[PDB]
Structures are given as C-alpha cells and as structure tokens.
Image: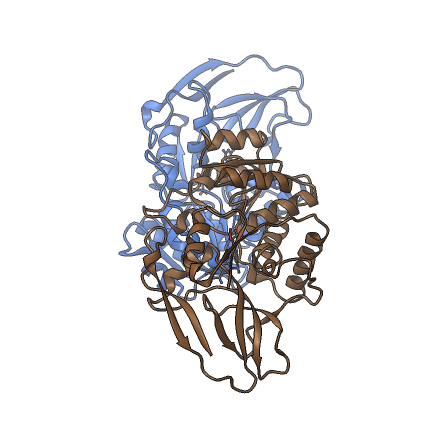
Chain colours: A blue, B brown
C-alpha cells in the first residue's frame, strides 16, 4: 500500500519551524510471512522528540508512537482488526514483524478514547506513576511541587498525588491551564509566566517547604524550587523542557550550598526502566483510576496527518490544552 | 588562664588573605563546677570553613575542631590528662561543660598520631566512609571518580574503594599529590591543573565511564564527569570546593539531557547524618584499616597556632601534601 511519512529535513535550531519537516510519499513492499501492515489511527507528539531528533540524520523519519490497527496480516497472533501500540515514527502506514508491538490492555473499554493509550493511560501516565511513587517515593501527606502541570505527565502526577493524600502545587504557562487544573483538585495553581515573583508565589503556596519535586522543566525554575525543599527532599528529574530549544548555554546550576545543607536526593529516570509485571500493574492502576473518576483527562485532537508538524510545534509552545494527539 | 583566638576581621573575597584574620588574646573565666579547661594540641583547617565563614559576623571566632587535653578539671568524668575532640573554634584554650565533647575511641593506640582523629580516623574519614559506601553504594567492581583526592576525604575514599575491590580514578592539584595517591593504590591519578583536556584524561582513565562519583569540587569539573557517568551512575555530593573561593557568577548546571538519558542518582550528604552505633562502627572500621595498612595516611603538620591562617590558605590552594593540621 501507500504511506505518508514526516522526515527531518533540517536539524532544529531553537524552536522547530515548518521548513524543518518534509512529507514524503512512498510505496511499501508486500507483506512477508510473519509480518503485518499497520494503519495509524492516532499518533502522538511529545517533548522528548525535540531532544531525540538531534540524534537523527537529516532525511530520517521523526520518531514517535501511535495507536494502529492491523489491516493486512501474515501473522496469526495479530489478525486483521487487532489494535496495537507501535513506534514506526511519524508515518500513516508501516510494516512490522510483530515483535516490536504491544497490544492494549485486554480490559480496555469503549467508554474512553483509544487515544488515551498514548496519554494518561499510556507512557505519559506511566511516567507520572513511577516518577512519583518510586523516584519521589511519596507515602502520604507530602507537599509535592510539579511544574508543566497541565501536560499529560504533570496533570497525572498531581492527581495520583491527591488520591494518595498529598498536597499539590502546580505551575503552568497560561491562565486557561490554571482553571483547568483547579477542576482537577490541585491545592494551588499559578501561571509562572505572569506571577510577579516565583519565589514569593512558591513560599506563599507552601511556607512549610516542599517534600517532593516532580521536575519536567529544569533551568532557573528548578533553582528556585530547590531553595524551598525540605531536608532530605526528593527530586524526580523527568524532563528539562525549558532547555530543549536553547540556543545559548545552560543557566546556572542550583546553589550547591543549599543542596548539601538540605542533603537533597535528585534522581533522573525514563519510563522504560520498568517493564514486565511492574509496567503492566501500573497500566491497570491508571485505567482503574480513570474509570473511577479519580484521574480525569483532556485531549487536544488535531485532524490530519499533514498537520503533525504543526501539532508538534504547538505542543512544545504549550499552546494546546490537554494531550496533543493527531488523528490520521 | 589566658587564650589566643583567631577571628574573622573581614569577609573573604575569593581566596582569603592574611589581612582577613585578626588574632586576639583574652582571659578565660574561672572553672565552674562540672567544667574543664581544654588546651589545644592539634587544630584542623578544612574546606568547609570557607563556606561557613560567610555566615559569621566580623569579629567572630573562626569555627573548627581540635584535639585537646584537659589541663584543669572540676568534672570527675573528664580528669586531668584526658584527650578529647572539641570544637571551640580556632583558639588555644577553652572551657567546656563536657556535653559538647567527644572522647577518642577506647581502643585508640599509641602507635598513631593523635592528629589522625581530625583526619583519616576523624570527620574527613567518616565523610569518605558514609559517602562512598552508603551514598554511592559501591558493591565491588565499580569504577569510582574522586576529586580533591589527596585530602583526607578523597584519600580515604580511594583506599576504601581499593579494599572493597573497585577501580579508582583520582584528580589532584599538584604533581607531588599525584605521586602520593599512586603509592596509596589509586589505579589512575592525574593533575587537573596541567592536563591538556579534562574530558580526554577522564576518558582514558575509564573509557567505559564511571559508576560512582564522589564529588568534593562541583562546577565545571563535575559537568565533565557527569558526561562520562554510566547509566544509573550515582553521585555523592559532598562538597563544591571549586565554588567556595569563586569570584564570578556560578557555572552552568549539568546538561540535563545527559542526566536524564543516563538516569543518574545524585544525593548530597553531611557526615552528621550518621550518629550513634553507625558512626562509632565506622570509626572503628577506619581505625582497623589504618592499623592493618589498608589505609595509609599523610599529615602536613604546621607548627605554631600563629600560623593557622597561613595553614588554612595553603590548604585551600592545594599547597600542602597530606591533611593540614596545626600543632599548637
Ligand atoms: C514514551 N515516553 C517515554 C520516553 C521518555 N523519554 C524518551 N527520551 C528519548 N530520547 N527517547 C524516547 N523514546 C523517550 N521515551 C514518553 C512520552 C511522552 C512523555 C511526555 O512528557 N509527554 C508530554 C506531552 C505533552 C502534550 O502533548 O501536551 C507530557 O508532558 O505529558 C514522556 C515520556
Ligand atoms: C567535620 N566535617 C564535617 C562537616 C562538613 N561540612 C560542614 N559544613 C559546615 N558548614 N559546618 C560544619 N561543621 C561542617 N562539618 C568535615 C571536616 C573536614 C572535611 C574535609 O573535606 N576536609 C578536607 C581537608 C583537606 C586538607 O586538610 O588537606 C579533606 O578533603 O580531607 C569534611 C567534613
């Protein structure tokens, strides 16, 4: 069949632009014995792609995951109609030998969008789950500071915190996202772009300090939060989105004297560290909390594979409310 | 009784200079019931004093620990002749009620200098012990990077690593210190002030990266080490000496894409976190290893209390081979 594919025409300089992407059309070969042909239903765009694109050669397909369905099959374990998670990149059709695929939860109901398998009940949600429960290690009652809180990771971090008995403080970059998070049960939410002083806003948000810091942003924002950590405070380093598009050198590191005196623990992680039983268990817990209403979700769905570069750029700028998903 | 005290005349700018200190003489009050008069035998100078001095008021005594002897006693628990660790600051004589004192290990032998209680078999050695064995969590076979490696901390870090079955790489500030660490069993030792490229020297010392980083220095040196940590590498943040005498703005932080991609664990600590049986067992272990030859030591004894500022400045600049101690 035919397929459309987004490739990296030019390595990004600062924020990506439209000319950095090129759409190519091609004819895929026939299926070989044991292979399947997959048709993309929903594709995701995520901040990590900004970092990962730097390792590609120009002309290479953009990396990324998708929900797809088997439309032709020479693999009896993956008959036509099967829905799978696949990571062929930004492409509408692809061929897989079945080994790099992942079926959805067998209990996946029709009452939630399939696209949540790329979001709250997918890798972003699993990232919040392990970053909070394992890396931060919350037990109950802690005060958690989480930035980029309106994204699919931060929004799930705060809600898992709330249903575990923890106070939550969230930072976002738009008053529109401020209201969205209050509805989700966040104790405090503020717009970091507009607050007069971040240090004063954080101190008022919790004069007692912060036990845990789920950090997606990094940079100067993290230095301010670090100064307000309690002793033995834990920092989960999930991302540094504020530096991914940087043209200049990295900002100053956190004041080492504070870090040592407070004896902070700071561990970075990637969701792929957990597999097997641990990963399956977390997925089921996320699905359960979605059905029970403890974890709400919101999506920004963009129609058209042709608009994937636009969805990626809007997502990086925070212009989209909810998980940015492209519908093929 | 009379005493001499070194005070902070002016807050340091960059490295200290002789004019930043002022020696004073005073008359101590009579011993009340339950008190002792302590005569300093050995006083230590250590890098942390540079940071702590910023919090002092001008005129205040410089902080620090000493090995002292009871020369007059109204406390039956501390008779005349008892050797204690005390922290009255840079002073030759002081009065204590006994609650803030620490007796030496009951098994302390007459075959080692008493000044080791301020070094290898004191707080520097305990910092190396807990930092390496618990914060880094060396298990045997790992490769360890330790800077400020010729100090009492770094020298103990490397030798505990050697006796636990690890490969050890050490950076130092002078050619003379390179030879000393070679004799102690360090696998690789180098002078970071004279190498063409820090990145290349570290690569050659361990082409496959570093499992553990015992960090006393921070700054740019640590950014380079972080770029060569293995996946799940662990960093014990003990000090940030490169920033203590800094004059310019703080250096950039570590590249978070490397920290996240490698999933590094980075925890700061201070030796006071461990007390009681844990601290006492560590001290006995250090004493054992010294008596077995598994931990060699070197001291740079400067004679004269009047030379304590010079000892402190030479120690800060890397001029002294071995733990800097002032003999009263
Ligand atoms: C699949 N996955 C794991 C993950 C993490 N880091 C990686 N890093 C690299 N280099 N490569 C990977 N494949 C990779 N994968 C993900 C996917 C999305 C998000 C994430 O943070 N998504 C945004 C999406 C924001 C939005 O769409 O509005 C969020 O904040 O929820 C994190 C981890
Ligand atoms: C007593 N102690 C614990 C410690 C650590 N940080 C502190 N920081 C502050 N502000 N205050 C303290 N009392 C303090 N104490 C110490 C003492 C010395 C060294 C230390 O690093 N000494 C140098 C001495 C170098 C030399 O003499 O050559 C070394 O590397 O061995 C560390 C911890």
Picture coordinates of residue B179, whole percent (x, y): 57, 38
As drawn, the residue found furthest toward the right would be B292
Q: Nearer the viewer, residue A201 or B229?
A: B229
Picture coordinates of residue A272, whole percent (x, y): 58, 38
Picture coordinates of residue A296, whole percent (x, y): 47, 51
Q: Nearer the viewer, residue B232 or A293?
A: B232
Classify residue A205 by image quadrant: bottom left
Would residue B135 be found to the left or right of residue A309 on screen?
right
**Residue B132 versus residue B303 in the image, above or below:** above
Q: Quadrant of the C terminus of chain A?
A: top left
Picture coordinates of residue A152, whole percent (x, y): 46, 45
**x 41%, y 27%: residue:** A305
Classify residue B72 by image quadrant: bottom right
Residue A66 showing in the rendered view: no
As drawn, the residue found furthest toward the bottom would be B33
**Residue A167 versus residue A131 in the image, above or below:** below
């Amino acid at each position: 069949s035919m397929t459309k594919t987004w490739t990296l025409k030019k390595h990004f300089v600062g924020y990506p632009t439209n000319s950095d992407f090129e759409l190519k059309t091609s004819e895929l070969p026939p299926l070989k014995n044991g292979e399947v042909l997959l048709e993309a239903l929903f594709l995701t765009v995520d901040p990590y792609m900004r970092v990962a694109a730097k390792r590609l050669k120009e002309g290479d397909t953009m990396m990324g995951q998708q929900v797809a369905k088997v439309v032709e099959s020479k693999n009896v374990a993956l008959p036509k109609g099967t829905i799978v998670l696949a990571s062929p990149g930004w492409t509408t059709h692809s061929i897989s030998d079945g080994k790099d695929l992942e079926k959805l939860l067998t209990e996946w109901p029709d009452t939630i969008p399939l696209s949540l398998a790329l979001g709250t009940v997918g890798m972003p949600g699993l990232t919040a789950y392990f970053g909070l429960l394992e890396i931060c290690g919350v037990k109950g009652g802690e005060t958690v500071m989480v930035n980029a809180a309106a994204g699919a990771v931060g929004s799930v971090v705060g809600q898992i915190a709330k249903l575990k008995g923890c106070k939550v403080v969230g930072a976002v970059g738009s008053d529109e996202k401020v209201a969205y998070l209050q509805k989700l049960g966040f104790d405090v939410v503020f717009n970091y772009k507009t607050v007069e002083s971040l240090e004063e806003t954080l101190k008022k948000a919790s004069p007692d300090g912060y036990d845990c810091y789920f950090d997606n942003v990094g940079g100067e924002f993290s230095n301010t939060v670090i100064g307000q950590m309690k002793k033995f405070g834990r920092i989960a380093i999930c991302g540094a989105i504020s530096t991914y598009n940087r043209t200049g050198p990295l900002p100053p590191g956190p004041p080492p004297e504070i870090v040592i005196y407070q004896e902070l623990r700071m561990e970075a992680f990637v969701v792929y560290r957990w597999q097997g039983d641990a990963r399956q268990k977390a997925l089921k817990d996320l699905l359960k909390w979605v059905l029970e209403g403890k974890i709400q979700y919101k999506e920004y769905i963009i129609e058209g594979f042709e608009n994937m570069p636009a969805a990626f750029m809007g997502m990086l700028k925070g212009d989209n409310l909810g998980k940015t998903i492209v519908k093929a």
